[PDB]
Length: 259
Ligand SMILES: Nc1ncnc2c1ncn2[C@@H]1O[C@H](COP(=O)(O)OP(=O)(O)OP(=O)(O)O)[C@@H](O)[C@H]1O
Ligand SMILES: [Mg+2]
Image (cartoon, rainbow, N blue to C red; front, side, top):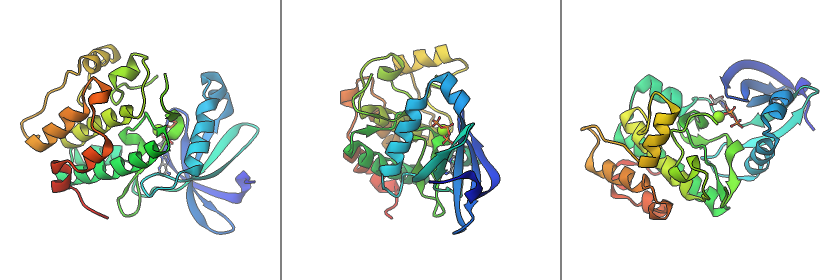
């Protein structure tokens, strides 16, 4: 259905590897939204037309308040256009740059929102695999929305920064839902500390740190946080808590908010 002439394009919202995302308004209804614009050539060269379909299939059909809606799509001679829900307060990545580190209640709140959203996804055998702060968007209430479903896959199943990926994944092995639990632990640490726990100056060093699960806490991280993170960041996937154990963890319950 949709054509480019249906939209007034405005301000650029962000760039990814593939997406060049703009603010946009639909002329008839004046509906503000975001258009994610991708180049067919690029997609063709990098060979990710599958990721495009998954992203469209998965994301058009989920419905949860902490997951970003994709409303539709259309294409040009030259480009593909995804019609997305607009997240007006930007990324958790920009929040963290601006704030440096989050206190325990913002952190806990975000983890709660992530863990419900992921609970919902996993309910449908969907694993996201790319839960990074630049793909975590903020709605008008400051509520966290998971975006960028191009990496998602039905579970189980067999590029850029490695920081959020678990051992089983950077090493090739089979993985399932528990990937998203490891990433939740990396996010929890990053929110509190301000850098992810396996950060390094090189990919190869990072790879080592993840496979050795080589991380330490600064002094200011508290015992309840250390406990949640240590549990999520276990090498062995089967040893990572389910999402309900996360949601009930005394540190989450002590520090997070309800809707
Ligand atoms: N709905 C939105 N509202 C506000 N900003 C957005 C929205 N969608 C994307 N952005 C901004 O643009 C950046 C790129 O978006 P996105 O992650 O969808 O592209 P990508 O990472 O290139 O995607 P893919 O993983 O499918 O190849 C985001 O990290 C974010 O800064
Ligand atoms: Mg992205």
